[PDB]
Length: 113
Image (cartoon, rainbow, N blue to C red; front, side):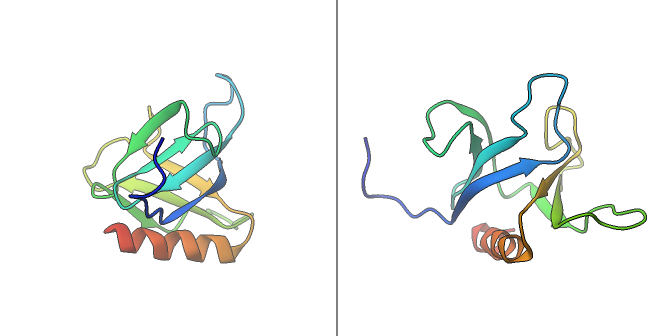
């Protein structure tokens, strides 16, 4: 397909804490943050794109812990006072360790967030 003309910013297997369980599982998806937009595919092959989301109408902030957090997870809300996901207003992306989160964040800024 295409070899050059590429410049990925960040990609990896993340887990959508707040996802539609009842309707199929595989909470884990292949997120690929690119200078253009951030899309998540079933795998790191980018064959059947599930849904593409821009990085101009999005925003990152502290996740609602209420009492106490259980892991490094960041929520993403749309600055256009709209639902980021099908129905969810903010997708809770949980990472393995802080190192990952710190990176993902710094990467977003580069895109324009």
